[PDB]
Image (cartoon, rainbow, N blue to C red; front, side):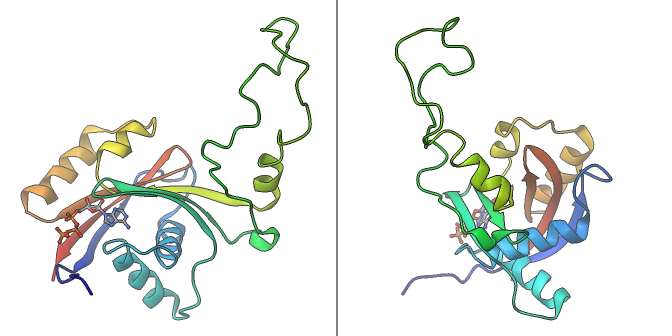
Length: 185
Ligand SMILES: Nc1ncnc2c1ncn2[C@@H]1O[C@H](COP(=O)(O)OP(=O)(O)OP(=O)(O)O)[C@@H](O)[C@H]1O
């Protein structure tokens, strides 16, 4: 029992990774299938925009998220080979080894070390259980994810904010894929 009355509606989309990685139709598919499995108030407008395009309802498979209030969210979304089912426990930290392993005799010989247990155990899991790193929202995480922002998308962005609407970006596997304009209903 809580509020959800300030409803958002998706109003314009533009692409940035054109010809290089992902196209507009796969962009709206991966955002709409991610928000089909999330619990957010805003990105679910793209869930409908996708569901109404696909004419199917049966969209969204497993997600491994990291969420923030106001600043957007990040996750790993599968469907392409999700038939393995992943181990996801604390995995953004879950370390193979907090020590040397490329050439120990040249770099800090503390120990004997493990060389197969836990090492590769998460990488070979993901490389068979094929998956996709995606994030969406705000503007500061769009900076912090190692990306570059251009003066034309910024002139397009602040303009929707000047018009008093909701103005956000979408990133994928350390690339910028595109941007979204949204309004209130
Ligand atoms: N699924 C989501 N994906 C990305 N960003 C999201 C998501 N849900 C919310 N946001 C972020 O929320 C920000 C807007 O915050 P705002 O305070 O307007 O929302 P709200 O908290 O729902 O509003 P209200 O003040 O009515 O509670 C956007 O810039 C957007 O990035």
